[PDB]
Length: 308
Length: 308
Ligand SMILES: NC(=O)c1ccc[n+]([C@@H]2O[C@H](COP(=O)([O-])OP(=O)(O)OC[C@H]3O[C@@H](n4cnc5c(N)ncnc54)[C@H](O)[C@@H]3O)[C@@H](O)[C@H]2O)c1
Ligand SMILES: NC(=O)c1ccc[n+]([C@@H]2O[C@H](COP(=O)([O-])OP(=O)(O)OC[C@H]3O[C@@H](n4cnc5c(N)ncnc54)[C@H](O)[C@@H]3O)[C@@H](O)[C@H]2O)c1
Ligand SMILES: [Zn+2]
Ligand SMILES: [Zn+2]
Image (cartoon, rainbow over all chains, first blue to last red):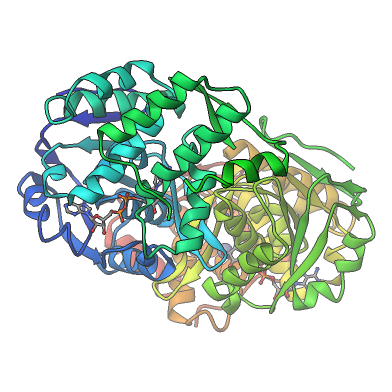
């Protein structure tokens, strides 16, 4: 069991989920898929005054006020107070909704994150950045609310679909190319099946030191791909995978990355089978990044002439 | 203008509203009554990049999600970001809605509270407590959001009704009897119209020095009166006025208040027309309070039945 610390709360827990002892009532919030796979795993180890379950339907489209209201109403129905706890058993969609629901319920109550997806373990459960989607855009209504404790177990990752798993892997490389050169070297040489525990541990420490601009590597182009397709074609991690390549073309054109650096990142994406032919944040090196702003339109078009 | 400092965050500005020059876009939120009385007063001395007004209907029944959604949507319509500002021009209902809307919009933006009611100038302004009402109860969904600046002008208080003004005095006496002996003696010997500024200044200081139990003096009984009457007959200050007297009956029976001290508070409420006939936290003399939790039911029932 590995315990990464932050500033100056709280405590992340890598490894098997331990026996959680609580002296107050707890509300578990999960999705339709996770509740039929990993809810027996949590309720086997949970001890509290009263435990009730609220289930949101699986999907990004359910990340709204309607589901947020349901989480709040379930907390009101079992009469939760200022000493109560909310438990998030799911991906980034669940953890953001529960964290925002707990922040506004009785002006702020404790909540615990137990991420199931690879992306949520390496990014979403860390930081306290919570929110919901609105008709005006994604994640524009939210709050900064830090969880009491984060529990990361590799057992939840085994039930994930390979396409959803690889989408999380593309997000790990994204953080590696901009922050940690040592994580790149691990992904280049070592097989992920043999060092999954070591990869996440390094990925969490990146986000722990972060908690910012830099995690948006391949997001400016990746957002544009999802807005043109639309969200019917690619998963978020797949769109960033193409977005990183588009960002690498702009970084090579501006003289930020060398030809060998451009190939090195693209070879690592090829190693994990993350090349997808379709159809602002750029690296200054393998393990570093720079913020580019005032870039000529013709330089962008020259990069956009690659499609790809 | 006099400038009371809280601790580090923000400054109160007690007196005539000065020129507010801003380098960011601003959204003013007011109610139907205040907008037709005091909105021009603010607009003439406000300078910003863009100024738009959102008006909610006057009343306690409009303190909900429906009005909160409108405040957020108006901010989205004029394209407000994390640098933008919200302006609250109204009573405690407006300030709580705007403060909660600003706390969730782009995960937290700056907001300036300009209270118009006497209640909001002495209680709702300083604290950071924001929120809205739900079908499950009042002020159960909210957040702790500190304002950028508070502006208290006595010019807004002149348009208030007699009933609304005297109900705001009930909270001043509440804070005086439990914290400041000198403020009790000021209210007893001086006319309020002669030292209204000095009374507010001391009321802000008490609220500032506390920030907590003790501000709920007459709230335990006052909530029971409001729930029995279905929030129909009395205002919040009027129900607390009876609640303070009910608390005075329990404090007199325990020996916490002398008969002379008991009559002093009753005559103070009589001076501000706060006697309304019947049909935890009690004052320890004048200027002090005590938390009583283990009071026998027989004593509480003897306080009921309307004597003393
Ligand atoms: N700062 C932050 O907190 C931050 C950072 C990154 C992402 N996010 C947010 O997180 C969201 C993305 O999260 P995500 O990638 O987890 O998507 P997701 O939560 O929607 O999960 C993807 C799908 O996988 C399924 N799933 C989850 N766990 C499973 C399990 N263990 N076994 C089988 N299937 C499982 C879910 O049903 C879901 O439909 C985005 O909406 C984004 O806004 C927030
Ligand atoms: N901790 C806190 O922030 C805190 C403290 C006290 C009260 N509150 C909240 O505030 C609410 C009570 O506030 P309130 O007493 O101001 O009620 P209110 O905001 O509804 O104001 C009373 C009425 O007077 C009118 N009015 C306001 N300003 C006026 C003006 N200058 N001239 C003429 N009319 C005017 C309004 O239209 C309103 O209908 C409660 O619902 C409570 O939840 C919060
Ligand atoms: Zn992301
Ligand atoms: Zn009130």
